[PDB]
Every structure is written in structure tokens, then in C-alpha cells.
Image (tube, rainbow, N blue to C red):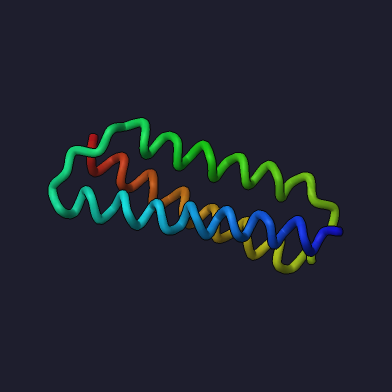
Length: 84
């Protein structure tokens, strides 16, 4: 069912959301964060987007999750840029 599938993505995006904050905290505290951290986070967010793309829905929460992902992607870009 679509509902379960969207919920599954949400759970994964939650984990990624926590990870993004952790990366921001590391940078804020002056640690040199490897570029792969930002790129892996971006990649995993993209994979979640693909999963949502394939969910035929439920459509409201799906669209909500897409927006959440786009926001996280922007946050990651900003971190990466800050460390470039």
C-alpha cells in the first residue's frame, strides 16, 4: 500500500535529517568534514526522492515528503559550499 511506502520513506528521511544536523554541528564546532559526507547525504536523499517518484498514491504526505527532501538538499548544499 502507498501509505506504508510513504511512511517508510519518511522514516529514512528522518534519519537523514538527523545526520544533516550532525554534519552541521561538526562544521560549527570547527571539524574538517570530508566531502563524501555531504555527497553521500545528498545521494541518499536523492534515492528517497526516487522511491517517492515510484509510489502511485497518500499523495498529500508524499508531496509533503518531497518538499522536506528538497529543503534538506538545500541545507546540504549550503554546508558543502561552506566547507569548500
